[PDB]
Amino acid sequence: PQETLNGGITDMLTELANFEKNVSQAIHKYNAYRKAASVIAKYPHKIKSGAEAKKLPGVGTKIAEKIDEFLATGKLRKLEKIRQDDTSSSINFLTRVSGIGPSAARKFVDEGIKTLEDLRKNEDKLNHHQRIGLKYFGDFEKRIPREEMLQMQDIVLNEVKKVDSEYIATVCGSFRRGAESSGDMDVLLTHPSFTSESKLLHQVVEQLQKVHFITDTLSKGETKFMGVCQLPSKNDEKEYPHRRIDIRLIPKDQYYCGVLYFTGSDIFNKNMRAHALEKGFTINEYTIRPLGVTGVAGEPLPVDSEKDIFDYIQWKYREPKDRS
DNA sequence: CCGACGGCGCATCAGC
DNA sequence: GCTGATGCGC
DNA sequence: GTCGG
Ligand SMILES: *CC[C@H](OP(*)(=O)O)[C@H](O)COP(=O)(O)O
Ligand code: NA
Ligand code: NA
């Protein structure tokens, strides 16, 4: 539906969501306002009253009253007052830096650090993650066109197999669901030597650094890498933006459940878990397990493919691109 | 009325 | 030195 | 902030 339908309302609710998350530190209100923004963005009518919006799930009495104020006045006094508070504005802005959440933003503004320039002058007060978030502030806010994601996928899948031909790597997220653009690249990796019962990530990260694909590290442990990458451009050509890449090393016996989980969408996964439950199975990120007659989860079932999960619960396979 | 609302993996701090 | 809490991103 | 036991 065209943004001109309810765009005023959905912008107001997104602004309130960001305020609750970044300033109030109220993650459950942030999610309530996001959920309300999302249901209203999908609604194929121009909302005429709060009462009409209130019929939608995730819209209750308070968001109805805000919509009535916005429809009558073209504004919300609560937001006009928030926009006049320079301290709220600074806290909200600093959370755009990866590694700066609501706590760090408030600590920074309370010691007079409010701008990107203030952060650059005070690098000693930033952790490693926040320094890299600052270094790539603009690039990290750019979307990744699908054509670039295809090129990135080709480097990652090929370089992983050069480390060891037995690795399996799958790019998940929006990209796997067939999105025309992505926020980041989320790679799930496994190897038959790694199961839930017994250097693998380090060697893959090392290879991707050696061919100058991975440029920086935000965090790295035994099973999760978060960092920065860049497509190679030909000499004299315009450089590609730096991109966020995550790499998750999953036990082989949990791998396809992970692929299903990190592919989504969220609504799809929720509908799939519910369907499994009525069929007598419980699905989480790691496993599919049969439920006994009193609701006790049994042993994990063997899963050798994503399709194996859909077969257990007798659902027809939804292609990754038919899950949003 | 009032608790749930995802929760893991990593970096870093608090406390011992 | 260690354990456990918190902040953070996804 | 909304939902639901
Ligand atoms: C927007 C109305 C609020 O809904 P939530 O419980 O955040 C409250 O009813 C009043 O909040 P105020 O806008 O701070 O007065
Ligand atoms: Na509603
Ligand atoms: Na941030």
Image: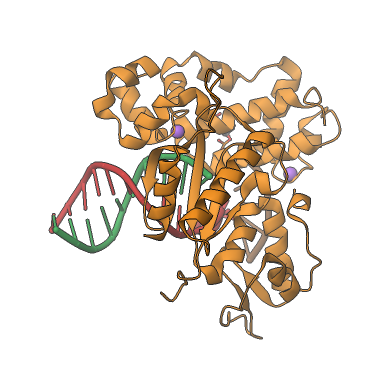
Chain colours: A orange, B red, C green, D brown
Closer to us: A298 or A131: A131
Q: For residue A212, say whether it is visible.
A: yes
Question: Residue at coordinates 70% horizontally, 38% vertically from top-left?
Answer: A38
Residue found at x 63% / y 72%: A304
Where residue A62 sits: x, y (%)? 65, 35
Identify the residue at image location x=56%, y=82%: A299
Q: Position of residue A132 (x, y in %)?
A: 38, 31
Direction from residue A90 to residue A28 in the image, left or right: right
Q: Quadrant of ligand 1?
A: top right
Q: Residue furthest bottom?
A: A293
Q: Which percent across, then down, holds residue A289?
A: 61, 77
Q: Quadrant of residue A8?
A: top right
Query: Which residue is the extreme one toward the right?
Result: A45
Q: Is residue A115 visible?
A: no
Depth check, front residue: A313 or A218: A218
Determine the residue located farthest toward the front in the rendered image.
Answer: A235
Q: Is residue A40 above or below residue A280?
A: above
Counting from the top left corner in percent of width and height, residue A214 is at: 45, 39
Say left or right for A91 vs A294.
left
Against A221, residue A48 (above or below) is above
* Left or right, A52 with reference to D3: right
**Quarter of the image where one finds residue A259:** bottom right
Q: Quadrant of residue A301?
A: bottom right
Q: How many marks?
A: 0
What residue do we see at 50% from left, 35% from top?
A21
